[PDB]
Image: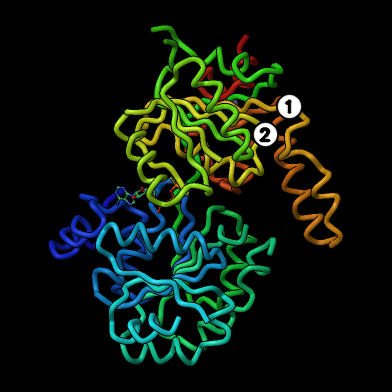
Amino acid sequence: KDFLWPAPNEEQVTCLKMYFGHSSFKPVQWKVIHSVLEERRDNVAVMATGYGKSLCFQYPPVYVGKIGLVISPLISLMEDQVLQLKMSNIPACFLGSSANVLTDIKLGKYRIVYVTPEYCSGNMGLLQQLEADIGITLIAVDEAHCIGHDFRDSFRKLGSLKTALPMVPIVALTATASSSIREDIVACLNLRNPQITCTGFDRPNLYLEVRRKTGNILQDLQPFLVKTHWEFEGPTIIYCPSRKMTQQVTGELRKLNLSCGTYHAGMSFSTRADIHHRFVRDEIQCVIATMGINKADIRQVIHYGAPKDMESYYQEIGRAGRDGLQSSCHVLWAPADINLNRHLLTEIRNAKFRLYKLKMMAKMEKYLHSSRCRRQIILSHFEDKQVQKASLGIMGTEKCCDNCRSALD
Ligand SMILES: Nc1ncnc2c1ncn2[C@@H]1O[C@H](COP(=O)(O)OP(=O)(O)OP(O)(O)=S)[C@@H](O)[C@H]1O
Ligand SMILES: [Zn+2]
């Protein structure tokens, strides 16, 4: 149910507004936050993209004014989150093998402390000292940050956190309902009677289509344009596989006077914040991207070129129709696309990582070539086997996907 129990009190709701700008907690967020704060319980939160997984670990230490330890091997992503938190008046730091920051962590100056798994393995005694002196509200581990080609490959070394900090709850975030992966998480992290919550993975308001490329950027994108200078039907994100393609597509759209912005990891935090703000305010109609985009009313997502893998594809299309209204997500691809080029995978000498990447690429290729319901493929991929009635209602209809629509011809 979407009934929050117990109800967030006045101190909790005003804190949420002051530090995060939100007026209410979402149901799965609240289940996790409450369990961490009141029950001090480990949690495995299976959360679909765009739900609000980050609040699960950022809010509790901010509310009690203690430390949330966020463990990830993605150093540049953590450095960027420090800056997002800074803009909300939440002090955060990255702690690594950091003389001026460790002294300040011991003084209570930081709410969120980002560390790599490598750092944790060598400094358990230091983390025990922080828990004894200040208190650690929670430890957060995101399974998705293992994109090192496995949760075990990325976080194997964390099988000592729970033994060093037995009373500190761990919140493990995952973007898949796979029982095998949940078992891998519980076992690797030594979770004690964890609370398991899941959001479900369908987004019924997204029409899914896959179409082959025609041999020219403007020729491929022309069908998405409506007359006025021509423009898209609504706010649109175009995902490209490389910074070069992002600039090529941007250059072509600008020949048609489309209002565009680019969004990639080569840009600074401040330049990305400006594009995001302008897209949110509808001062630009299209963002061409290669670090998410949160906007309520994205009406169209286009992957210009085959996506990398099902997980990133799903996260990317998930930015669409966050308001619940009808949106469309189209993949324009060709077998020669760089994300299906087996050469760089075939170059890997190691047998294990060459097999993992080849398996991911094969799953993506099978989805692109499929004549089956695209929605069912996605739901099955994320092992969301208990399909919701809403999903059964959308599937098979003209608004589900291109294959469902052509079966109705
Ligand atoms: N309680 C809330 N109410 C309204 N918005 C929220 C709430 N919690 C989080 N959000 C927003 O939801 C968006 C998604 O949250 P994130 O924790 O960044 O999840 P994410 O799956 O990494 O998002 P994407 O998919 O990468 S855009 C962010 O803009 C949050 O600010
Ligand atoms: Zn379908």
How many numbered marks, from 0 up?
A: 2
Residue 325 at x, y = what percent?
37, 27
The residue lying toward the viewer, choosing from 107 and 358, is 107
Residue 272 vs residue 41, the one in the foreground? 272
Q: Residue lying furthest left in this view?
A: 10
The label on residue 306 is: 2
Q: Give the amino acid at mark 1.
A: Ala
Within the image, what quadrant is residue 92 found in? bottom left
Q: Are marks 2 and 1 in contact (CB under 8 Å)?
A: yes
In primary-sequence order, the first of circles 2 and 1 is 2
What percent of the width, then of the height, locates residue 53?
41, 56
Marking on residue 149: none
Q: Is residue 318 visible?
A: yes
Which residue is painted at 62% across and 13% down in the image?
219
> Is 179 drawn above or below residue 291 in the view shown?
below
| SS under mark 1 | loop
